[PDB]
Length: 89
Length: 80
Ligand SMILES: CCCCCCCCCCCCCCCCCC(=O)OC[C@H](COP(=O)(O)OCCN)OC(=O)CCCCCCCCCCCCCCCCC
Image (tube, rainbow over all chains, first blue to last red; front, side):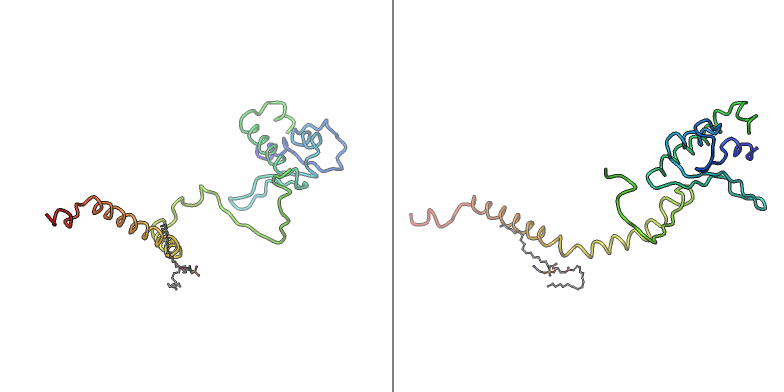
């Protein structure tokens, strides 16, 4: 299920050809506001533990905005998940 | 113009922090608060206190000098 959640957020780097029509809202707002150079989501698993989260590369003057948008997406997945994005994931 | 991102140029500095939910809000409050307060007051007491000490002495001297200024001089009404 957490993997499906990562599939909702997805990955992005600057060489992606989707433009502003990317299905991920984080990737779409990153392209629209020129915020990040790249981001990715990870679910690293070890024996009954692990790290679930996101890693992004960007310049300095965007960092806080990226964090804000990233956290918003997580809270949206905690509060307002719909069936269409779940099917896509 | 002056916000986070363009304040200073810092190189090779590592900061470590923990969550406030992970650590105590009062970690050894009295046992390290008392010697730290004692150290601060012994580093500042000689600069701070003696002016207020001599204010207390001047205040007491002025009040008692006014009180004996209102006192009747016994040298008067002695000739007759
Ligand atoms: C010569 C210093 C000897 C010190 C011996 C003590 C032990 C020292 C070694 C152990 C360490 C103990 C803790 C140290 C704490 C910090 C260091 C310290 O206290 O240093 C001494 C301090 C600073 O020394 P310094 O400024 O160099 O002296 C010039 C004096 N004008 O200087 C002082 O604290 C002295 C302050 C004296 C102030 C006198 C003020 C008199 C006049 C007050 C007038 C107020 C108004 C009166 C009314 C006016 C109108 C009528």
